[PDB]
Image (cartoon, rainbow, N blue to C red):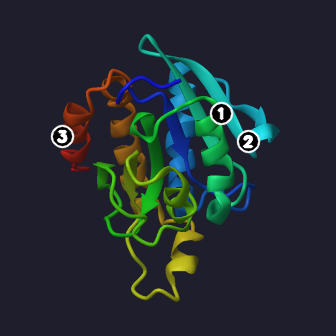
Amino acid sequence: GSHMSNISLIVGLGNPGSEYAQTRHNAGFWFVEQLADKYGITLKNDPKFHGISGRGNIEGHDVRLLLPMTYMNRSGQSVVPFSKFYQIAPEAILIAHDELDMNPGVIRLKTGGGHGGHNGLRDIVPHIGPNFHRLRIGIGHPGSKERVSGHVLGKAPSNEQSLMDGAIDHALSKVKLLVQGQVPQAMNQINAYKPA
């Protein structure tokens, strides 16, 4: 299975369907789809693990990509059995997700900690614990908890979308460090990203 903190599983969180593909809550899908295209990893139907998944070589490392197709609040129904079947320790998992607590154009690599109310991460941490890496893609916050639904299931305005796209692009350039186990350097270089 996995080997130390050499990231060998990259999960993108999101909802399935054309109606969610452009929503802020699908930021993780954007990252992983763009990473799959960057490295020529096929993302194929994986009914066994209720997702779409790939396997391929990233910079000389055998890496698996996973998009749960469970709906966001059931992400664990894909991530938990998939990571256990391939013996992937949480320390070798990167989960990319939308982060309400950061501005569009802000992106950070975080190791461990809480779901911070994220309904996707909420379905995962109870099973494998918190010690996986997260690519937190800033989406901004809508004010109140009643509006969180409408924000994350919203399609960002073009200014916000541009800022997220730039942050995601930046992050793609740092996956080489992550798959080589250089989490500290990758954290500094991702966290340092500014849009302008």
Residue 94, x across and y down, in percent = 44, 40
Q: Residue at x 56, y 61 (%)?
A: 120
Q: Give the CA distance from mark 2 to mark 3.
A: 33 Å
Q: Give the CA distance from mark 1 to mark 2.
A: 10 Å
Q: Which quadrant holds residue 174?
A: top left
> Under tag 1, what secondary structure?
helix
Residue 23 located left or right of residue 143 = right
**What is the three-letter code of the residue carrying label 2?**
Phe
Q: Residues within 10 Å of mark 3 (few under 14, many from 20)?
A: few
Q: Residue furthest right?
A: 47
Q: Residue at x 52, y 62 (%)?
A: 24
Q: Residue at x 63, y 61 (%)?
A: 72
The residue identified by callout 1 is 85
> Under tag 2, what secondary structure?
helix
Residue 65, x across and y down, in percent = 58, 33
The residue identified by callout 3 is 188
Of 19 and 60, the residue lying toward us: 60
Q: Is residue 65 above or below residue 59?
A: below
Badge 1 or badge 2: first in the primary sequence: 2
Of 85 and 13, the residue lying toward us: 85
**What is the three-letter code of the residue carrying label 3?**
Asn
Q: Residues within 10 Å of mark 1 (few under 14, many from 20)?
A: few
Q: Which quadrant holds residue 171?
A: top left
Q: Residue at x 45, y 53 (%)?
A: 129
- Marks 1 and 2: CB-CB under 8 Å? yes
Badge 3 or badge 1: first in the primary sequence: 1
In the picture, the disc for residue 49 is: 2
Residue 132, x across and y down, in percent = 40, 45
Q: Nearer the viewer, mark 2 or mark 3?
A: 2
